[PDB]
Amino acid sequence: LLEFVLDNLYLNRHTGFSQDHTPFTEGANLRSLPGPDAEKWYSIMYPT
Amino acid sequence: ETQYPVDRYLDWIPSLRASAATAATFAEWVNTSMKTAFDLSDMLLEPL
């Protein structure tokens, strides 16, 4: 338990969002990671 | 959505709610178009 706490000592830097260009969502701003293949993250973040 | 009153009879014409950045980029394209239309070699409303 202590090590899990130790491993979680981080500061979360404010991320960025992009307006949705598709009709899957109503032009929502999705947190956008740097690098490609974030769509797997997008689908997981919003199963809806 | 701006407080300045303007008549819209073509809201039926399809359009989404762009993010402020999206509107600004569309505006920048309209501005480049206007400069080329008047053949403007100088910056227009760049502070704007």
Image (cartoon, coloured by chain):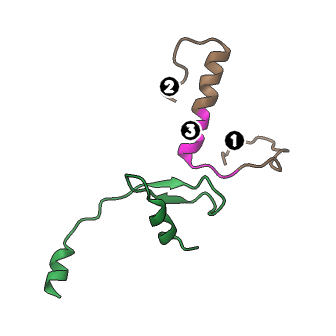
Chain colours: A green, B brown
The answer to which of B43 and A24 lies nearer the viewer is: A24
**Rendering coords of residue A21 (x, y %):** 61, 52
The vertical placement of B10 against B34, above or below, is: below
Q: What stretch is highlighted in magenta?
A: B16-27
Chain ID at mark 1 = B
Would you say A33 lies left or right of B2 here? left
Q: Going 58% across and 55% down the picture, which residue do you hit? A: A20
Q: Mark 1: which secondary structure?
A: loop
Chain ID at mark 2 = B
Q: Mark 3: which secondary structure?
A: helix
Q: Which amino acid does label 3 sit on?
A: Ala
Q: Going 68% across and 16% down the picture, which residue do you hit? A: B37
Chain ID at mark 3 = B
The vertical placement of B44 against A33, above or below, is: above
Mark 1 / mark 2, whichever is N-terminal: 1
Mark 3 / mark 2, whichever is N-terminal: 3
Same chain for the residues at labels 1 and 3, yes or no?
yes
Mark carried by residue B40: none
* Mark 1 neighbour density, 10 Å: few (under 14) some (14–19) many (20 or more): few
Q: Distance between the residues labelled 1 and 3?
A: 17 Å
Query: Which quadrant of the figure has residue B24?
Result: top right
Q: Going 72% across and 49% down the picture, which residue do you hit? A: B15
Would you say B2 lies left or right of A44 here? right
Mark 1 / mark 3, whichever is N-terminal: 1
The vertical placement of B39 against B47, above or below, is: above
Q: How far apart are marks 3 and 2 (CA)?
A: 12 Å
Q: Going 76% across and 40% down the picture, which residue do you hit? A: B6
Mark carried by residue B24: 3
Q: Is residue B6 magenta?
A: no
Same chain for the residues at labels 1 and 2, yes or no?
yes
The vertical placement of A8 against B5, above or below, is: below
Residue at the spot of label 2 = B46
